[PDB]
Image (cartoon, rainbow, N blue to C red):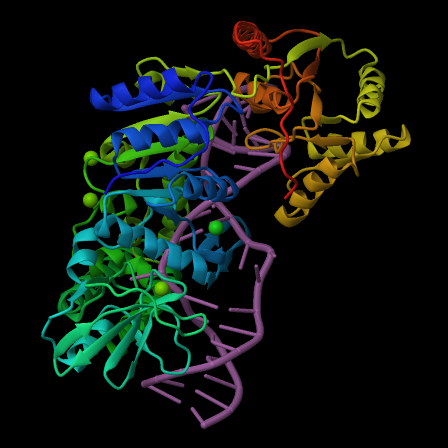
Length: 591
DNA sequence: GCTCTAGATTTTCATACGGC
DNA sequence: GCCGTATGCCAATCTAGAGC
Ligand SMILES: [Cl-]
Ligand SMILES: [Mg+2]
Ligand SMILES: [Mg+2]
Ligand SMILES: [Mg+2]
């Protein structure tokens, strides 16, 4: 395939040079590069240009699913002729199996699956074999266990007009790859028959079923079919039907796997019983033998993922197969918000290991359950072909592995990194209150950041006493109601929002002209250099953007952020001067 | 170095049950 | 043994500080 970028506009401002640097580094074979793109500079359009120029299948990794969704929307509009795909957790809810020693409690695994997300997951994986012009937006789900891509590929049922194959032989192979017959409710992951037509709804597709028409053992035709109404659509010459699960469990391997699980259990029970952990072994035997009977009286068992490694016959310690393995060897990775996303990726292994080791220590699971896991960060490193880290505040790992940075600060809209004032703590709430009132005069909103949920709630109350319209925003408030609070800020219900750590990455509020950082000098994660610069960027979407940092000293963290903001402004002033640009505030749609 | 602390996101091969 | 349906808010992750 071949990527076709589609937009009205050309690259502008800093975008051209940025695109050129990243493309040349990629072509020279450089492994790690870093796009130091300041906020609201059109970072998704820049990276799309790179993808379009180098024409490699690409994985965009995001640290959260809201941002994941936006990237996926924007990229769908930029590449409407290409396979833009989505790959995140497909669980409506999920609690893992866990044991909590401090409160001596076992917690059952509970789950519930979202059908749309599973459909997208299958569209994503199948796309990577059907064609080369694929971009997948993904969460850290990308580093979790799937079945091997080789097995996933060889189980495909490939069909072409002219083929000779027994009607029932197709059907019986479809069942092998996890499809169900269903003449009543014809939906994805199911098939049916209507005389000569064998109608197949692939696992990757919402509304568009295949219709394979037979004459004896021949295939006279194949047809994509709109299943909203029932009408027929275009007539293909071939089609590929991929498995309706990323996990194969065939009996041929399962028989030996059972005796391997059987013999790991013996050894572990002897181990536990020897150490006077008699309760633990009784636990381990009761679950393992029950699961093993289910494994003999059925294909499945409960918690089957715990026996991943045995059921695959792969050795102890094995690195799992993942989405990354489904990509070609010359693929490309974009890491969105790398300073937050990479630490998250690092820690997926740690938390999973922690949780599973206590299950194993208390005899809920065998030691081989540790091999059912995500990648370690080191295993992620070894699977990188080439990678681009995007962030306004790139972290240590990105800088240390990249040959300097591609800097992109000039915004196509000419908006400046705001000015910053530093004021004393003496009489700070009154100074702020008056400064908010001037903003309410100009119909401009304000963000205030404190250190705690308690302080954010107390200031909201106190600002209500002063007659200011205001809400607090922190993580006690569920996602749905946060969307609504932010919506209601823009419409004008509130002139102020008080927060802690939800007022940085991916918050475009054009109406905000003031950002108030309280306790600006209290050293810690909330007032580190990066979180400081990220908070400052909330005021860079409005032409009268301003920052007040209340503090009595100026920390090292404060002085780097002040200096790097000033420098960025000065460069943006000069570009604006050269081109006669007067900064204009962002007109963005509500909802 | 170990053990707290604050406010943050993400992830994880559904399953027990009653009525057939 | 098969199948349709009601069901949960239950962990350990991160950074970068503070006491020892
Ligand atoms: Cl979506
Ligand atoms: Mg499934
Ligand atoms: Mg491997
Ligand atoms: Mg590679």
